[PDB]
Every structure is written in C-alpha cells, then in structure tokens.
Amino acid sequence: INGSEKVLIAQEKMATNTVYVFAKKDSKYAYTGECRSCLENSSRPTSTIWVSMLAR
Amino acid sequence: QPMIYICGECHTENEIKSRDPIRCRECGYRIMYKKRTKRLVVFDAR
Amino acid sequence: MNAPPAFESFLLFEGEKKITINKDTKVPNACLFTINKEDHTLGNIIKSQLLKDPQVLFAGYKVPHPLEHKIIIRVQTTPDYSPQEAFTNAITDLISELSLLEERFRVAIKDKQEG
Amino acid sequence: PYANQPTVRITELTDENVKFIIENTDLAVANSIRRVFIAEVPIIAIDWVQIDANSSVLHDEFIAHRLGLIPLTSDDIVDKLQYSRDCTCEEFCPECSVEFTLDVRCNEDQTRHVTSRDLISNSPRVIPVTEQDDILIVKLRKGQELRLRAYAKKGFGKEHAKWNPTAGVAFEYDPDNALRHTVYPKPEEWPKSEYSELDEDESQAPYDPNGKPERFYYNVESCGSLRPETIVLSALSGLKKKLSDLQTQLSHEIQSDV
Amino acid sequence: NELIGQTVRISQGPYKGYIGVVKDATESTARVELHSTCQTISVDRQRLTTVG
Amino acid sequence: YRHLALLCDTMTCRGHLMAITRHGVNRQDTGPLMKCSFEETVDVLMEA
Amino acid sequence: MIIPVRCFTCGKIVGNKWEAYLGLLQAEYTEGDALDALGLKRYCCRRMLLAHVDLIEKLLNYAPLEK
Amino acid sequence: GRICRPLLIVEKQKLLLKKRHIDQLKEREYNNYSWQDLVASGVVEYIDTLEEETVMLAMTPDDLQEKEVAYCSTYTHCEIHPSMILGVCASIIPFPDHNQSPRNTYQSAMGKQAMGVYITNFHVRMDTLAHVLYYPQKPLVTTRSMEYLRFRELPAGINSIVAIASYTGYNQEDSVIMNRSAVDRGFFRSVFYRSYKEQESKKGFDQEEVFEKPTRETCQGMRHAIYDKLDDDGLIAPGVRVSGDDVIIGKTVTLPENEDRRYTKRDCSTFLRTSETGIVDQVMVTLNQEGYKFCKIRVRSVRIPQIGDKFASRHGQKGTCGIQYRQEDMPFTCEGITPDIIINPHAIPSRMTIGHLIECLQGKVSANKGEIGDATPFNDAVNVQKISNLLSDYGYHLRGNEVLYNGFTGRKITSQIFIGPTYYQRL
Amino acid sequence: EITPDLWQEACWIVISSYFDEKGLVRQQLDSFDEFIQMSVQRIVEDA
Amino acid sequence: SLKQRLKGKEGRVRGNLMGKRVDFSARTVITPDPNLSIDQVGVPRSIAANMTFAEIVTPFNIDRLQELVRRGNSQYPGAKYIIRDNGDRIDLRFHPKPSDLHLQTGYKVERHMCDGDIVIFNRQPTLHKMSMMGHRVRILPWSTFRLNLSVTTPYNADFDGDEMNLHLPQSLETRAEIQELAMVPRMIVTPQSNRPVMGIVQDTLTAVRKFTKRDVFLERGEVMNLLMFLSTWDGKVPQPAILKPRPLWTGKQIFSLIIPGHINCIRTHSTHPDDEDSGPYKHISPGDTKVVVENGELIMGILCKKSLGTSAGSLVHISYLEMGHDITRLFYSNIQTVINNWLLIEGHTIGIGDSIADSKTYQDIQNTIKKAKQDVIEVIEKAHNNELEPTPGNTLRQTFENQVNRILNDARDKTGSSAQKSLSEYNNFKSMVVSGAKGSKINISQVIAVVGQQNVEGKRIPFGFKHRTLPHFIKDDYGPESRGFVENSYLAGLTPTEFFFHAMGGREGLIDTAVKTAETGYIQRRLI
Ligand SMILES: [Mg+2]
Ligand SMILES: [Zn+2]
Ligand SMILES: [Zn+2]
Ligand SMILES: [Zn+2]
C-alpha cells in the first residue's frame, strides 16, 4: 500500500454464537449469561443478549 | 548535458532531459537507475 | 565517528616526548619513566629485566588506561646507584640477549635446513 | 645484574609453521617475542584501493575489505620498503608501495570467479601467495565487471590485522605445571600437553618453589605472507630496534636532565 | 573559498594517501572529508594535493 | 525514621487526614501555582 | 555472504578453501573428514567453513541493474 | 477463526503413523505423497482448543504406549513433537528448556532485532533502515526447526569463540570484551542502508517543486552546504561520499511573489540526515502514482563494531562492547586460539542461562567433530554427560575448560577459563 | 509396521512434509484466499 | 482547546514549565571503565567538541583562551563563540577576520569542554538523589560515556544498552555549586537508610574475596605489579609475611596498603559459622571468616559483601565517616584497580563444570524426589478415601493443598541443601554466592538439583482445561508433575509440560515487573 508493506495483525475476540456464564461479583447480578450472537454472512454486526440472575 | 540513466528492466541506457517524462525507449519502463559517478573513489582497505 | 585512527598506537606527534623522566619525591632514588606510544610489549620486558638487578628495590609498570597509549615504569634503586643507570643497563642487557638469541636462531635454521 | 643466555632448539621447520623451544630466558621476554610475532612484524598488504568500476553484487567497501586481507609474498621486499608515511615521494612510489591492477569483466554464462590470481603486480616478487587454490575475492554474473588499482604498503599488526603474518602462535611454558601457576581442581580430568613427559599414571608434576618459568615452547604458523622463520628473525630484529630507539630517546632525555 | 569542493589527496603525514573532499578551507588547516572511512579530519594545507 | 516521621507529620499537621491526592493536597492554602502544579491545573486557576 | 578471506580468530587464510570444501563434500566425505583433508586443525578455523552459508550464489541469480 | 494444530491419532494403544507412511513420505517429489495425503489417510488430524478439553494426548510414543505401572492407557492423540509448541523466534534458541523462561522471552525479543541478511533481493529493495551483515553464519549449535524457518539460508549472526572470563574489567555489568584483530577481519562488520524519497508537486502555479541544482545567486534561502556533489538534475550520482548536512536532492520550489524583485525560487531540499555519513549506494528515478517525477536515493554506510555496540547471544545474554583489545592483548589457549568475545562470568548465575554453557560445550564438540550439532529442546538423546564424553575424545577437558594464558604478562591464568564457540547476534 | 526407536528421525520427516506443504503463513494466504474467493460474493449477494 | 493545552501531562504546567527541553546536554550509551575514578565520566570528543563552557577572559587565562580562539572551532580544544563586553556574539566556526579575535579582560569565550570540567550525569527514571550526580570530565577516544563500576549501584545502570543524560552547568557559580553539593564522593552515604549506596560491584567483589583469603601468596614481581596501581601508596614495600624460604607476601598485606588512614572495624564473612563465637577459636578463626580491620590494617577475615558492600557499618561506611570523602573516593578507586590487576593473574570464570555434581549427589537428589513424590501420592490416596482429616480453620481441600505444598517445599529445601553441600570449594557458583556479588543459594539449587514448584498467583498451576492442567494429564490429577512441580534442574533440562509450567511462572514475573512501574512512579510523584 503506497509502497509500504502492511501486515494485518490477527485480532482476538470472544467466540460468537456461544453461551457464556460469568459472574459480575461487583454488580447487582449473581450470575450473568451472554451470547454474542452473530449470523454468518450477515452485514449487521453482533448483538449481545444478556440473561442474568439478580443477586439478593 | 544529458544525464544517462539505465532503464531498469531493460538494462540499456539512454539520455534524459530536464522536464522530461521518465520513459524508456525500448518498452517504456518507468524506473531508471542513475549511472555510477565518474569521479574517483578511494578506499582504505581497512 | 569518534574512532581513534589506527596510527595512534605507535606514532608520536610534534610536542610529544617519547620518554619523560620525573624524579619521585616520596622515597629517595626513585623515578617515573613515562613512555609515550608503547604498551605491555615494552614495559613488561623492562620490568622483568629490572627485577634481575640486585640493586633495584622496586620495579613496576602500569598503563594508566588502555585507550591512551602510554606506560609508566617506576624504578626505585639502592642509594649510590641511580635508577636512570639501572634503566639504561636494562635496555642494553635486553639488546644483548636478543642479539645473542637472534644469532642462535640463525644457527638453528642453518642446522635444520641443511640436515 | 645481567641478561641470561637463551638458547634455541628447533623441533621442526615446514613451509607453514616452525616449532621451537627457547630455554634460559624470562617469561616476559618470551611473551614479548610472541606479541611481536603477532603485531610488530611488518609485511606488505593492500591499503589503497581505487575502484575504477564495479558492477558486482558485493559493494565497493566489501571488495576493498576483502582485498585488504589477502596475504602477499613479502619475504625480502619488506626490509627494503620504507613506510609509506615516511617516504619523501609524491605520495606514492615504488619505494614505499607495490602496484596491483585488477580488470575483470565476465562475458560468459558461467559464474566467473575473480580470484587472487587476477591481481597483477608490477613487482614480480610481491605476488599473492596462491597446490592450493586461489583466494576468492568476488564471483561475477555475466554482464558484471570490476576494475581497480590497489597500492600495497608496509605496515604491522598493531595498525591493522591485515598486516599480521601469523596464522597462529602457540606458546606454552611448563606443560606439567611444576610451577603450579594454574591450579586444577581435579587434575585427573585434564589432558596432558604435547610436551608432557609424565607417565599416564601421573596427572601433574610435583611442585617446586624454587623453580621459575623456562623452556618456552612455540609453534609459529605463518599465513603465507612470510616464511615462518623470517617471522621470527624479523620479530627479533624489530624488538631490538624498538629497544634501541627507546635507548636513544633515553640518552637524549638523560643528557637533557644533566 | 576556492579550495572548498575540490577533491584532494593527503600527500604527507600519518594520513598519507587518503582521498577526500574539502568541507571547509582556512588560512591554515583545511578540513578534508575522508572517502575511505566515516570521519572528517583537519590537515595542514601544505599536505593536501588537489586531484584533477 | 526521619522520613517516616516527616511524612506522617505532614499528613497530620492540619488536624485531619490529608490524603495525598488532589482531594487532600488541593484543599490546603498553599498557593494557586503550587496547587495547579499538581494534577488539576486549570480548575485550580479558575477557582483562584 | 562470500567466504571470509581469513579465519576471524587466527587469521589463517580460509578464503581459498571453500570451493575445494564443496568438492570434497560432493566427493562423498564427511564434513569432519573434508575439513582436515583441507588441513584445518583448530576448531575456530573449522567453524569458518563448517558453518558458512554461501549466500552469494543466491545474489547472482538476479539480473544486474547496471549493464 | 478457530485455532487448531495437527496431532497424530492413536488407536487402541498404537500410533497410526506406520512405517509405510515414512517410506512414502521420505520419497517426496517422486510419489507426490504430501502432508495432505497423510491427513487424507486418517493418520493426523487438526485438533482445536475446545476439542483439546476432550482428548487424551500422548506426549511422545516411546514412553506413553508401552506398558508400565499404567498412567491412563486410554490415549486418543499423540503430540507430533514437543518442540512444535514454540514460536518462530523461540525456535532458534538452542536448548531453551535449559534456560530460565524470562531469558527465553528476552531472546525472543532480541532475535527480532538481530542484524542479518533480511531478504535475498535486498539490492533491489529501497527499504528505509536496512541492516545487513557481511559474513553471516549458520549456528554450529542448531535446532531441527531452523531447517523449516530457513534460518540456515538467511541467517543472523556469527559463530564466535567466546570465553567466559573475568578480565581487565570491561566485561563488568552486562558488557563484553571484543577482539580488535577479529573485527579487522570482518567480524560483525555490518552495512546500514537508508533510503530517501522525494517527488515534486505540479500545483496551481503558486508553488512548483522541481529537481535542479540550486544556485546561490538565483535561489533564496539556500543553506550553507556543498551543492557541487549534485549532478545536473539535482541528484547525487551513486558512489559519492556524503556526510551530515550534505545535500542529496537538489529541489527548488517556486515563489509566487517573484513578480509581486530579482530574487526567485526558494530552496526546498532534503539533506542527508545529520550525524550520519556514508556512500550513496544507488539512485532510482521514476514516476509516482500521480505521474510526477519521484526519486529515491539509498545511501550506504558500513558499521564496524565499536564499543557501545550492542551484541547478544541466543539466550537473552545481551551486552554492549566494553572494549576492543588487539590479538596480542587478548588471552590465548595452549594453541593459538584467542577469544573473539569475552563475556562476564557474573552474567550467568542469577540469570540462569545454563543453555548458553551447553551451547558453548556442544559448539566445541560440533566444531571439532565437523558436524552442525543438534539442540532441539526435548531430546533425551543429548544431555551434558554425552556432550562431555564426546568432547573428551578430541583431546580437551571434559567440561570445556581450557588453560588460557594471559595476553599481557604471559603467566598462565590460575583459574581454567571456560571457552568455546557460541552464536552471537549483532543487534 | 510401527516405528520403535527410529521415531526421532521419523517425526521430523512429517514436520518437514508439513512445512513443505503448508508453509509458515497459510493463515494469511488462506484467509485472504477464502475472503476474495467466496466472502466478497457473499457480501454482494447478501446486500 | 486552551484548557486542553494546559491540562495534560504534555501541557504547559507539567510539560513545559516543570519539565522542559534543555540546551547543553548529551545522551549516549554507557560502557564500563575501571581505570578512572568514581567521580570521573569519560565523555567522547564529538560530544565535548559540541558542548561549551562560557569562560570569562581574565589576565590569568588570557593567553590560554587566546590560543584556543586561534585554534578556532573543530581544532578540538578550542572554542566556537566569543562574546563581547556588550553581549555581542562572534562565531568562530565561520572564520572571521583576525582583527576581532583579540581578547581583553571581560570577554566571554564559549570554549569546548576539556578534562576536569564538571557535568551532571543521570538516568531516567531518576528515583533518588544519587540517580543524578556530578562527575569530572575525562576525554576518552571512543563514542560512549565511560563511567566507573561502583557508580552503577546508585544509578541502577547495567550497561546493556543503557544510555545516560549528561547536563553541563554553564555558569561558574553553578559549577561550584555542583562541586560542593552533588559530587559522587559527597553522595556516598545516603540519607534514606544511613548506609552507603556505592559499595563494591560484582567482579571486584569476587576477586577481592578470593584475594583476601588466607592461602593467597604473592611473588615479589606480582606485588610490585599490584603496588603500581595504588594511588595512595607512600613508596614503601611492606615486610613480607613469609621471609624465608622465599619472600612471599600475603594478599591481606596489600589490602592493608589499600585501607586508608587508621580505621577499625569488625565484621563477619557471609559463611561465618554461628557456633564459632560460642566455643573456642572466636579470635583465631579457623575458617578465616571473622573480618578485623585494625589500625588501618587488615588483621584477618575474608571480605564479602557484608564487609565492602552497601550494608551499614561496613568497611566503606566507616571509611566515609572516620576518614574524609575524598579519601573514600581514593579507597574505591584503589580497590577496583589493584583487585582487577590481581584478577588478571588469578583469573575467574564460570562454566559447565561448575554446574555438575558428582553421581552420589545426583543419587541423593533422585532418591529425595522419589521419596517426596511417593509421599505426595500417599497423601492423595488418603485424601480420596476421606482418611485425610481437615486442619481447624480451613476446608479439606485447603488442608490437602497445605500438605502437598509442605511436602514439595520440604523436598525443594532438602534437595537444595544436599546439592549445596557438594561444591568442593572451587565451584564458581559458590565463589559468586559466598562473596554475595551475584546470585544466591536458590540459583545453585535450581541449576544443580531441582527447579522446584512453579506457581501462578501464589498457588499451583490451575486447571485451565476441564479439571486437568494440560491435555496430557488425566482428569483430576493433583500430583506433583500434573500441577506444576518441576523435578528436573536447568542442567538436565525440563520436559515440555515442565517447560510450559515454568513459562507460566516466568510470565507471572514479567507481568509483575511490567505492571509495577507506572503505579510506583505515580506514588513517587504524589509523595514529592
Ligand atoms: Mg539496562
Ligand atoms: Zn530499454
Ligand atoms: Zn614513497
Ligand atoms: Zn583460526
């Protein structure tokens, strides 16, 4: 690119379309699930839904 | 007064002018290489 | 850049003395001989020859710095006997044994090449 | 109060090396004769390289470097040449230099090896040392060339390592360390020297306190620029010359003090 | 100055033989720019000799 | 002990705990240039 | 790139050995036999050929820019 | 985007990599039997990281399919070779399991910084900051994995006879004493190329750059430098010495108020970068994307190793050059061998690079035996006792120590200095 | 049959076959290859 | 904005008013030099031919300064600016006519700096007041700042590509101020912990520990070589400790020639037995491990880092307090020079012979690893069968982990002690550890015997996979090798699972080192 040799560094990310259960121990939620849902060959980006149990 | 440039891929040599677009005559190759200077060089063999 | 040129090891300049005698004042009969543009390949032989006199009480040499080309040979001799005399006898004794060594090396070559 | 009488015993003499034993001298005399083998022996080596043309894949300073380190036959000329910076000539002459000329263009599809043979002297005695093959200076593709003129001058090993006549100067005293200068932790593991004279039962010699270093064993292997015995003769002459000039300056300084 | 820019060959002294180009000229000691190594040296103008 | 005593004495030479932040150093009367030399620079000068 | 003219430690002229070293390798010797067939006793002279990579033969493939 | 790696496949307690696969796989370019034929044969397969949670992975087959007091005996896959867990820069380290792990990380940093022949077509490339080396060497102590990174074809660094000795005191605190005569024989003498690009800009007639030799009487703002080095087109011909604040590109831009007197177009020239010097290697003249004339000048400067120059081992053992002694000052063995480098003995015991010592020992064994020695990490066919028994046959001490003589006094050194060849990298 | 103790030279044969088949940069080349071969058409049709 | 121009660390207050770019300063790499005093820095010529001191023309120096102006610029010791009485600058680099190169009393001459000029030398990050000290210029040829070895310790500068900053004080008044406050002899003893900061660095310290042993004897020629390097020697060769059969000096006599004035200290060597001062021989030490310097002469004892180092009450601290501070500068320089020049005769190395124990020791190490490994396995089979009982205060799992960590730490300690009983007194690891110059007993234990338990966050290697640490181990494997204990040493090398667990522990150390820096610097900034 303009005579300059460019390298696309591979960028990590959380794996999409996969349910995860994490613990926001500082928030009001005991256990929070998530699923960074992203359909393959879809122009729209990912859209994370969270499913979280309240801590009381 | 013309400067002699070596025609990149062609490896032949040609004259050039001031305000002249840089083109070979053999195949119009755009990269010229300027010839080695005519003044003397001297190296200490160290 | 700041590379000293290669002739700084052995070439002197205008206003450089090859040898400088400075009479020591701490003890009697002692001198510092500052040799400019030399190294261990002179002062080591002079030190070892000055240790062979029975009249030299101290014979040492040091380089102040290995990037600056000078040595100092300190000589302390016995009183009645000048250290300059011990130094100029050490040089003559070295020239004596090296010329003798060179002649014996010549004779050994003539022995070896001629069977 | 005087100098002991040394003596020489030569064990072998080959066109590469000389192996000898110097007895009845001090350690510092012996080390200095080694250091004058390495440094203070003057030979003839290329020092002024004028590249007329170059098209080779190696750049100019690399070729001038490789022309520096080529040994030249200087067996009798180096005693006749003045040092270049000492001559009164118009900055180069045949009294302080040897002219070399290289003029090679590769006009063939084979890779043409510009070797040391292509260095052409005007002095028939000072030629590169290369039975053995020639010293490869630069390879050439078809179309490439190099032309240069190179002046060689007298110098010694302190100035640059291209004026070093010796390949290797092995030097050892007391090969069974009766002196115990080196102290082995377990002397059974240690291999015996070439000059050891102990039986294989014994590891190292018994200590003597009254001993001193003598019987110095040398192995002077030349690189080809000098015969290995004229390295030793030139070294002894150079060390005696350094000591004599030191004595002359000493006499001047003593006469200046008085 | 007239000397600056010329290519000179050091004709005397420890640097004898080196080719260079004068950066600065003085009434006394010119500064020669050595073609062989990377450095600039001051030399008396009696030593220098112009080449071509 | 000189250094520990000096630090513990500057933090308590005001009667209350002088926390070493902007929140404790920039509440004592020392000087607007001194107080703007620390982390909050423009706000100290605007207030002064 | 090209073979050094002198061994770095000794100063033994090793630059004339390289093509004969290649000849003794292709004539089915071991490398250790080829080195002391060329007569290199000291290991510092043996590393100079034993671990050389003759890179100039790669550089000669390219057509010369000047001609 | 998942990240997998190939593993062998283990039926009941046996590898599926039979001898016939090695027989068909040695004879490549003839049978056209590739890796992909072995993936097709159901012998290896790619396992990713999720599936590694549900796999029972044999490390090596010579230990882990033979009956013993059995560990699991339910292996599914077998690792091909453990040395393939390492990266590309941690693969060039000899014996990296003998080092400490911060030292391996630091070498992985330094191995990206070593000078060397970075590419084969470097004479065509107009790279900015090209560091190439005169006489690079392959390591005497190498791994098997350097054959596949092609490190023996474009290497970076020279095999050097180091000695590990306290000495005059210039290898004190991570520095090294070098040999002046070795350096004068081309040892790590490198060459640094730097290019310089400049084009002119045809604009709306108010400012118009053009390459020409600027004249003091014609051009304004012309800085006091030498302009007779330039050719007639405002460029340097190759093979011309330039130094700091020498011009390399004569370019003048026009001034819109030359009529709005007698003083015309201003100097806009690129000088050589100050406190640098060297010969102009080569100059190319061409057109850019925009059709404007455009010149690149690559300027060559060789770099002889001097003090302050930063060298490093293959183990994170960096250090600048403290001093350079000549050959007669450097110590020497019973034979004529002097060191090229002398490194600090105190650099070892807190850093704990024992792999440096083992590389040095295997280097003596390799340079004497006449073979490029093997230093794969997880081997078990090479430990230090076998290296010592191989060294003892060539007339040396078992553990590489060798009696150095002093270079100044000639009295042989009371301790026995560890000496031998390692592989040093110039950074 | 199997490889009893010449395994040490038999594994580097298959490492060499891997790096002669694949090479060191199959990630970059295969990723861009599948991009410009399939995914650009997928972007054009999915608009 | 304007508030954004002022508010930053790169702003006007902090970025330009507090810390600003300064003229008359140089930055190059440092490389060691032991042949110059502790307050001398060896600057290059091309730095010194570019940094100028404005010297006032007085009738004492008018001929000297006249000659330096006649040399002009780039005839190195000369000058570049000559400043008139009305503040008019005249160049000397552009070669003016000779009529205005005259000097009368009152002109300034900005001359190139020579030997003996004072400079300020520092290292970022400047932590304390001995990280920025005043040196005297020595002009040495090559292009680095050669500075001395014992000034490494206050600077924390380890020459592996470290470059330092050199400021020149321009006025004569600030030159005298730096000479009277910030000289490195006046910054030997620190106020933070009333002890010295210089000490004696590594190679001089091992060579002086080997030097001052009881069995070191010196021939007359070696004595005369060593006494050549004492700056403070009054020219009197001492009487030998051995007159007959051969005149033979002990190294403690030469070291008594080093020790200045008449100072009196009693210290203990690092391997002094604690049961020696109980019974007999408390004044005639059989190991020569009780340092007594007395009336300025080293009576007895071997000088480790507890004698010459930066510990308080050491020999150098008492040399600072009883004698002067110029005298301690001389003491440091004399130790460095004469002990390096003895070390040329002695020689000191380290090798692979120094990392190998005899086979009886290896059998002891392997028997201890096998015994402790079987003990961990039998603790595990007690833990599975609920026969392990919980320690009061924690769970059964934390009780188990205490048992396993206690057995493995006992194994590491017992193998470490059984390794270090087998150095045979010539092992150079022991030579550097006993002097305290570089390393510790743990490094000897890890090189010879066993690396030991690898840790991540203070506990063992966690189960990153499902209930196993690596996919080579069976699930729920709480054994030694599964959980990160490394039984191999650096001489034998690590197996790949042990290599990876070792790399984990090392990554934890590098994360600590890289994250520590910013928070510690911000704490320092808030405190100041
Ligand atoms: Mg550092
Ligand atoms: Zn053409
Ligand atoms: Zn002449
Ligand atoms: Zn050699």
Image: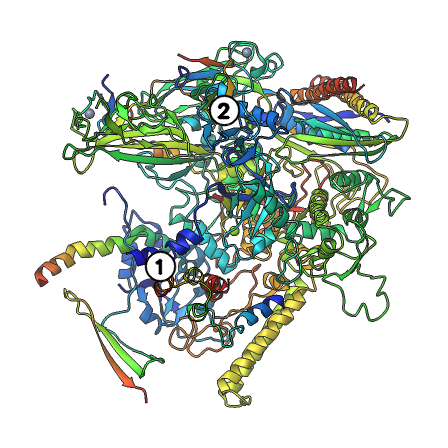
Indicate whether H62 appears above or below D107: below
Coordinates of residue D69 in the picture (x, y in percent):
51, 26
Q: Is residue H14 left or right of residue H387?
A: left
Indicate whether J402 appears above or below D128: below
Neighbour tally class for label 2: few under 14, some 14-19, many 20 plus, Cα within 10 Å: some
Coordinates of residue J12 in the picture (x, y in percent):
38, 53
Coordinates of residue H194 in the picture (x, y in percent):
36, 36
Residue D127 appears in the figure: yes
Neighbour tally class for label 1: few under 14, some 14-19, many 20 plus, Cα within 10 Å: many
Q: What is the secondary structure assignment of the residue under circle 2?
A: strand
Evaluate whether label 2 is on the same chain as label 1.
no
Residue D186 appears in the figure: no
Task: For marks 2 and 1, give the CA distance.
Answer: 50 Å
Chain under callout 1: J
Q: Which residue is mark 1?
A: J7
Splitting the image into 4 quarters, where does residue H268 fall?
top left
Chain under callout 2: E
What residue do we see at 40% from left, 34% from top?
H274
| Residues under numbered marks 2 and 1 in contact, where contact means CB atoms less than 8 Å apart | no
Q: Nearer the viewer, mark 2 or mark 1?
A: 1
Please state, as top left, top right, bottom left or bottom right, where the N terminus of chain H lies in the image: bottom left
**Amino acid carrying mark 2 in the image:** Ile
**Which quadrant of the picture is home to ligand 3?**
top right
**Amino acid carrying mark 1 in the image:** Lys
Q: Is residue I25 left or right of residue G48?
A: left
Q: Which residue is mark 2?
A: E41
Indicate whether H15 appears above or below J405: above
Q: Which residue is at the front of the view, J374 or F19?
A: F19
